[PDB]
Length: 51
Ligand SMILES: [Fe+3]
Image (cartoon, rainbow, N blue to C red; front, side, top):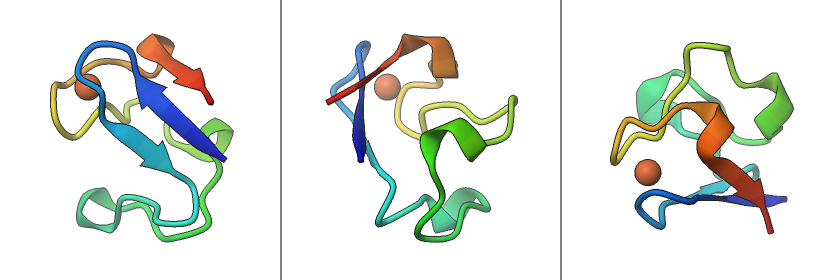
């Protein structure tokens, strides 16, 4: 799945993960740590929407 940051337009793609911030490819959004934030704008998880 993909999830968009409603603040900046960054797309969290589960197939890509976010390795530079400790998230390996294939990590589901719901599995992201509670303290993970948008790598671009710093928004909390609450500000993402599933596409
Ligand atoms: Fe963002």
